[PDB]
């Protein structure tokens, strides 16, 4: 049964061992001792643990086992931050993140199995709180990319999958935030009403459980939480940062029968005004680590600022011959050469460190 208030309150955030290991190896390739020590400070900043392949599901057990042992040893209640990201025909409007599951080859049933495997590890460790981000990009694409044939063909499956994950996770007391795009995707005034409709319907079909806490925004993106000085890339959009986006979405969601809360990714938001076009998302050059994870937010509607996308892990390959090459990853404002999405992109990480705002102290 669900407790009241902000679900992050009074919990220590478990630090990702996978990202810690990656940063450690990134730091070991950096010779400048002031940059090296700065790099190593990042494994101390909480990020979300992505389960983008079904071969990782058992690692959740290992993380929950580890977090439970920390809790027993310290007496400090722990919270593990995870991302559910493996819908069949994933990333239907792009090719950079492409997914192991196909709708043509038993995809929906395989996704159900993937969710059950996550659920079966979570059952093993009930004494630790979990916060989960559900399927980045999926529903966002249903609002704005129904024109794309692959997204149309995936719609039923996306909705069924997200609803299945929500009901299974909410049964086990996991706090969920469904991915809801960003200010430059759904904050456009035409997409605000249909977004509110869709997320409210998902909430309804998943059973209106209080463990379905709200939405996540700006995942794998670079938008400001709050900008005084406008970004000219946002020309035509009147909600040009994440707070305006949330302040315009929340009342509509309420009206559609869901008092949603929010969390906001700020992991690569340190530097604004680094894109020529607002739809440019792939390995954007010159980005920096942004506002640190905090429960001191500018709104009652926002539970937490977080780092969902772990900076340094690539968004997509720039190798034009690769099967998963997306032309957005070869843009002029993209850091090239880039390795496959998910894999370590060292020079990108280094710039994220160098461009950190607030700066990383050694
Ligand atoms: O945020 C990371 C994900 O983004 C993806 O692309 C989306 C862009 O991020 C988003 O800015 C853009 O928004 C469009 C909108 O669809 C349209 O209604 C409006 O008029 O113009 C905007 C242009 O700024 O949409 C795209 C998706 O089509 C990637 O697909 C995804 O892989 C990535 O994780
Ligand atoms: O399996 C490789 C790698 O995936 C990482 O998740 C990626 C995902 O693969 C990518 O498509 C998406 O755009 O970004 C996320 C986060 O970088 C995951 O974090 C790694 O642990 C994993 O090894
Ligand atoms: O600003 C555009 C930048 O794109 C990147 O891919 C390159 O590494 C930079 O040298 C270049 O200037």
Image: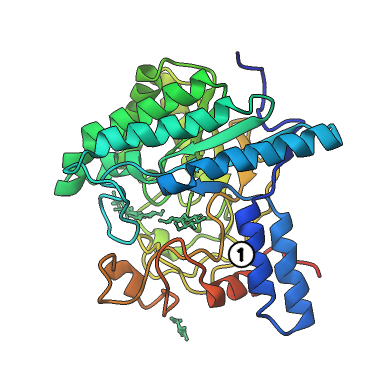
The residue under the point 41% across, 20% down is 255
**With respect to residue 263, does 197 lie above or below?**
above
Q: Is residue 137 left or right of residue 231?
A: left
Place of residue 350 in the rendered image (x, y in percent of width and height, measured from the top left): 61, 75
The residue under the point 31% across, 40% down is 191
The residue under the point 41% across, 49% down is 53
Q: Is residue 8 visible?
A: yes
Q: Would the CB of label 1 be found within 8 Å of ligand 2?
A: yes
In the picture of the structure, the residue carrying the numbered disc 1 is 22
Quadrant of the rendering where the C terminus is positioned: bottom right
Q: Is residue 296 visible?
A: no
Quarter residue 154 falls in? top left
**With respect to residue 44, does 214 lie above or below?**
above
Quadrant of the rendering where the N terminus is positioned: top right
The one nearer the camera, 315 or 5, is 315
Question: Circle 1 — which element?
Answer: helix
The one nearer the camera, 350 or 121, is 121
Quarter residue 303 falls in? top right
Place of residue 45 in the rendered image (x, y in percent of width and height, measured from the top left): 70, 54
Place of residue 20 in the rendered image (x, y in percent of width and height, measured from the top left): 67, 59
Q: Residue furthest right?
A: 74
Neighbour class for label 1 at 10 Å: few (<14), some, many (≥20)?
some
Q: Is residue 94 left or right of residue 132?
A: left
Quarter residue 129 falls in? top right
**With respect to residue 258, does 42 lie above or below?**
below
Q: Give the image's coloring scheme.
A: rainbow
In what quadrant does ligand 3 lie? bottom left
């Amino acid at each position: 049964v669900p407790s009241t208030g902000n679900p992050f309150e009074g919990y220590d955030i478990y630090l990702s061992p996978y990202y810690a290991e990656e940063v450690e190896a990134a730091a070991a390739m950096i010779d400048d001792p002031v940059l090296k020590a700065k790099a190593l400070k990042v494994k101390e900043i909480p990020t979300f643990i992505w389960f983008d392949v079904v071969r990782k599901t058992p690692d959740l057990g290992r993380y929950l086992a580890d977090a439970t042992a920390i809790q027993q040893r310290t007496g400090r209640k722990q919270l593990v931050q995870i991302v559910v990201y493996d819908l069949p025909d994933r990333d239907c409007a792009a090719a950079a993140s492409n997914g192991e599951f196909s709708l043509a080859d038993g995809g929906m049933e395989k996704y159900k199995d993937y969710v059950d495997r996550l659920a079966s590890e979570i059952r093993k460790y009930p004494d630790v709180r979990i916060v989960a981000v559900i399927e980045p990009d999926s529903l966002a694409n249903m609002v704005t990319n129904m024109n794309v044939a692959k997204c149309r063909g995936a719609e039923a499956a996306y909705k069924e999958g997200v609803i299945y994950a929500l009901r299974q996770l909410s049964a086990l007391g996991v706090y969920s935030y469904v991915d809801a795009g960003h200010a430059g995707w759904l904050g456009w005034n035409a997409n605000l009403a249909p977004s509110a409709r869709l997320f409210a319907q998902i909430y309804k079909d998943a059973g209106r459980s209080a463990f379905i806490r709200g939405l996540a925004t700006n995942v794998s993106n670079y938008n400001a939480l709050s900008a005084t000085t406008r970004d000219p890339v946002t020309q035509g959009n009147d909600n040009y940062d994440e707070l305006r986006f949330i302040n315009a979405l929340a009342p509509l969601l309420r009206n559609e029968g869901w008092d949603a809360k929010f969390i906001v990714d700020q992991g690569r938001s340190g530097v604004q005004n680094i894109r020529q076009e607002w739809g440019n998302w792939c390995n954007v050059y010159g980005a920096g680590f942004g506002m640190r994870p905090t429960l001191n937010t500018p709104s009652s509607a926002i539970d937490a600022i977080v780092w969902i996308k772990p900076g340094g892990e690539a968004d997509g390959t720039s190798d034009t011959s690769a099967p998963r090459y997306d032309t957005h990853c070869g843009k002029s404002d993209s850091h090239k050469p880039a390795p496959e999405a998910g894999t370590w992109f060292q020079e990108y990480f280094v710039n994220l460190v160098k461009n950190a705002n607030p700066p990383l102290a050694a």
